[PDB]
Image (cartoon, rainbow over all chains, first blue to last red; front, side):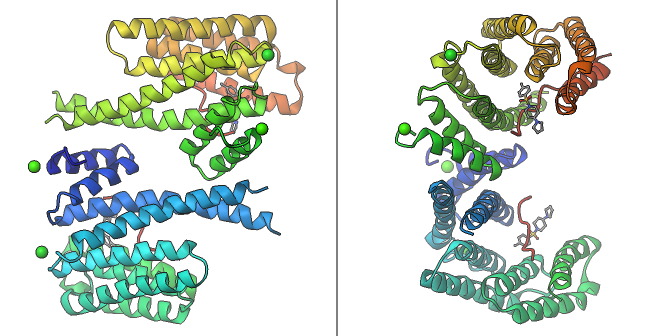
Length: 228
Length: 228
Length: 9
Length: 9
Ligand SMILES: *Cc1ccc(S(=O)(=O)N2CCC(N3CCCC3)CC2)cc1
Ligand SMILES: *Cc1ccc(S(=O)(=O)N2CCC(N3CCCC3)CC2)cc1
Ligand SMILES: [Ca+2]
Ligand SMILES: [Ca+2]
Ligand SMILES: [Cl-]
Ligand SMILES: [Cl-]
């Protein structure tokens, strides 16, 4: 998208979201990142929304195909097609990870931007881990863990316990523990401690911030209800 | 998809539908058509479902963008992006019309296959007409009309009034009259006559055929309720 | 005004 | 188990 203005790419990403054209949205936001400037809060959210929709569709398709393939193992077409979708999913994760490494993370000096990008890095390694098989899985899992852990360390030092990015990071890291790392007790402990520390800080918030934080706290509670 | 077996393309189209990967589904069915053999009833439905999903997403996005563009006319980005989506939509319609012309229609000798493909031809010209502007619109509209009319003539001679393809053809031709040709009275007359002739033939049907026909009859009734 | 949905086999 | 939906701006 090298010939399109940065501001036009951002405007088109917003239009693509309204039109539910998420592949287009991701391509516009990739072009905007590649202009080389840092992203604002709103622009970071557009980048994340675009890719979460693209990879979310791929993950849902991969799960459907994997389920059919496993039942078939109780011609080569189901495996071949699951592999095709898997390769496409891995390519999207690699693209996002490449944008974070060149050069979003290294230029992110404020806590809000750096935590946001490291949470993304953990998420896309987690999506790689969902489809990885073997010892490849081990290094991919450690990459997710390391990204989430660095984000957590910054978030606990630099953000209040009600900050929505801090809360969403803790939510997703708890899902990592439960679903990827086979550490359900660590998942439950993280979700509980996060919820309780946020509850105790709600009194400091405006009505609008209260709504933002409690929405994500309910997600932590929903997981705790499922896990206990 | 020239290197993939016909039977594998069909199997993958079914998997792609289950995974809600409709672009893949359409590409697999295009490859199957290009093998040069005629399509069975089930295969024709897979081809139609694949492309109706692809073009349905494009039409919905085009409508969102066109609405934003019109309100903006009460920078160039909204128009440029609407044009991009429009061009993509036109390309998909041209692809389907190309498969029908090379060579699905000319090899379709049974009424069921020939009516099915001519209904498709009317539908994809109708989708072209939805986005066409000017005298281009006139010839595109006439192409839709001519395809639907030939299908109607065959269907009335060769199929019972309850046949689901005959009913769906009449439904879509009535929508053509109402939405494209500015002929609401012709739309209402066609929907009414179609519904009434089907009602009078229901007594001939099994329980399962009755369910198939009455489902589409309800769609005719839903339109009549909106139009009168 | 609704045409055949046509999006599920 | 649910992560942040993250699919709407
Ligand atoms: C991981 C993560 C990402 C974003 C946020 S957020 O910016 O505080 N926010 C994004 C919008 C969401 N709304 C939009 C419509 C429904 C929810 C809410 C969360 C937090 C954590
Ligand atoms: C234009 C048209 C196309 C197909 C048919 S159909 O074969 O009789 N049929 C397709 C399946 C539909 N079901 C699937 C799930 C819900 C509805 C019903 C119509 C008729 C007309
Ligand atoms: Ca510039
Ligand atoms: Ca062969
Ligand atoms: Cl910086
Ligand atoms: Cl033939």
